[PDB]
Image (cartoon, rainbow, N blue to C red; front, side):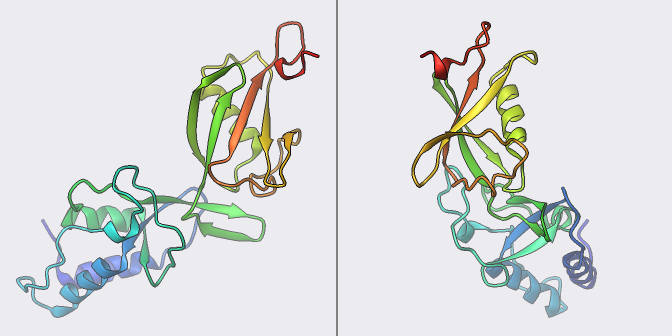
Length: 212
């Protein structure tokens, strides 16, 4: 059920010409594989040995255990971006190499710019009153601190009637309370992997971090 080489070229190429819309998923394709696919498709022969095989993004991964992206990857040199539908077509036709996961990234909106966020921020969220339980959660730099707060609340099974707030160590460094929840993680100047401690208000109205 695989289309003509002509159709593949046109359908995938036209895919690349898709305008960025907030919340839409795009996918990374390793440059080498894409060039081989391109060679195959432009060859004009469906039975040619230039058949690219399963989509192989091995060169894009740091390690094949957590499947993190290598740092400092550049669009056009290391990878090509395809929209979700174009990606789905490509996958249906050629499949994924071995146990490789798809590299899905979201289109985000920053003040003045819309872009596919290839490197989202990872935060280490911990409850102040349950420090054994640390969750690594992935956010967007465009996301608000308040969004981090609710996500933490639901990940830590926190009830809705309770007040929570965030503490964090910047690289200055100092431990501060994130009192302005209406700002982006970018305005908050957060590094990926940064520890963020969520605290729940006690019944008496006091905070566990302020018992003195």
